[PDB]
Length: 135
Ligand SMILES: O=P(O)(O)O[C@@H]1[C@@H](OP(=O)(O)OP(=O)(O)O)[C@H](OP(=O)(O)O)[C@@H](OP(=O)(O)O)[C@H](O)[C@H]1OP(=O)(O)O
Ligand SMILES: [Cl-]
Ligand SMILES: [Cl-]
Ligand SMILES: [F-]
Ligand SMILES: [Mg+2]
Ligand SMILES: [Mg+2]
Ligand SMILES: [Mg+2]
Image 1: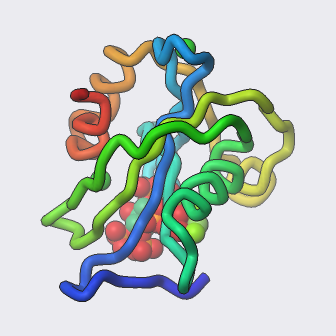
Image 2: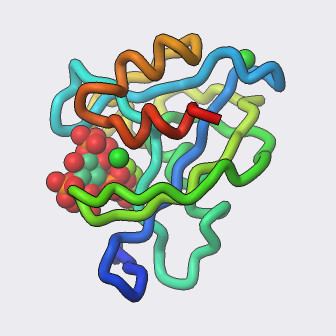
């Protein structure tokens, strides 16, 4: 549970764009913990000495209950307002697990979205997460 930081003091995070298939047309979002009627891209803090790709896959399993085939690093995205820096990877989902950690613990929800709908629901409070899909 120990948070880690870059040398500028930004929190180190990792996340995946969890796609339903190699066509990358539908992505899995999860509910916000603060505001459960909102959607976010699953992700979270890198542990000490943890590789970003390992952190990304681990947080997706914890938060979204999925596993799959890790793909490319999309990019490294800074949130200046919230002082964090996130490595974002593609993950092609191959396993959808029931009763996952955040479902059991906080009633976290998950849902598939077409890319243009994911961008729409992320824009108001997670505009940097909406920018993950730009490329
Ligand atoms: O609970 P999570 O994992 O979904 O994500 C929370 C961040 O957790 P994050 O996803 O970065 O980490 P993890 O708990 O490892 O997933 C947390 O970050 P932190 O303050 O470091 O706890 C941040 O708190 P902030 O400090 O006010 O920015 C919250 O806003 C954010 O909540 P959300 O985006 O509404 O779901
Ligand atoms: Cl898809
Ligand atoms: Cl963000
Ligand atoms: F977490
Ligand atoms: Mg988490
Ligand atoms: Mg998180
Ligand atoms: Mg975490």
